Structure formats: structure tokens, C-alpha cells
Amino acid sequence: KTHVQLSLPVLQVRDVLVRGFGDSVEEVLSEARQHLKDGTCGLVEVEKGVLPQLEQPYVFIKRSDAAPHGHVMVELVAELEGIQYGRSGETLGVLVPHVGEIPVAYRKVLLRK
């Protein structure tokens, strides 16, 4: 399938134990996609002071369309030193590894895979 229905645990930035996916744009996108498939991917909602507490490169989920079965359609865009790799809509949040942190909510998304 080109799209996959996921429910992503929404984590508080100060709970996050592994604050990024790796060390290159290509690695963080690769690792994000693997964790999304393996159900080991969390979402941090972006507000003032969140991104500086996470590790670059960042992986964002961004709205790709204006929401089948409650699931917002999203795609991945990476960012490193203010350059983004991808073009998409509004940020729903920043992806991080999930290693058992307790979420505050779930974000239903349809991921273009």
C-alpha cells in the first residue's frame, strides 16, 4: 500500500529519551520510516523551545492533503541547519524514536509510504 493508517503516541519533549533518528538527512528519513513501520515512532508537537531540545537532523510529519477515517494524510520532510529536504503542508510535529515513554495523546495519520 502507498498509504498506511498509523496512531502515533504524542510525547512531551522532556520525556523523550532518544532525541533523534541519526546523523544525516538520509539516515533520519530512513530510520523514521523503519520506526513508523515497526510501531516504534513517537510524535512531539512543535512549540517555542521544543526543537532546540531535540537533535538535528529533524524529521517532520507535514499535512500532504485537506482526512480518511479521521487519519490526516502526512509525508516526511527532514531539516538540517535550516535546509528542508521535501516540500509539504503544515507541521503536525517532529518524529522521534519511541522507547516506552508514556504519551499524552495519539495522532491518527495516513502516512505516504
Image: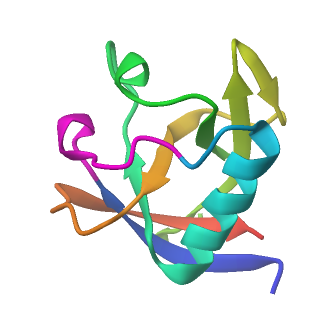
Please tell me which residue is depicted at 64% across the width and 32% down the height of the picture. Answer: 57
Q: How many marks?
A: 0
Q: Is residue 88 magenta?
A: no
Q: Quadrant of the C terminus?
A: bottom right
Nearer-the-camera pick, 101 or 17: 17
Query: Main SS type for the magenta part?
Result: loop
Q: Is residue 82 left or right of residue 14?
A: right
Where residue 100 appears, as percent x and y from the top left, is 24, 69
12 shown above or below 106: above
Q: Is residue 19 magenta?
A: yes
Q: Quadrant of the N terminus?
A: bottom right
96 shown above or below 59: below
Where residue 29 appears, as percent x and y from the top left, is 72, 51
Q: Is residue 38 left or right of residue 78?
A: left
Residue 32 visible in the snapshot: yes
- Which segment did they paint magenta? 11-20
Q: Is residue 78 left or right of residue 12?
A: right
Nearer-the-camera pick, 4 or 73: 4
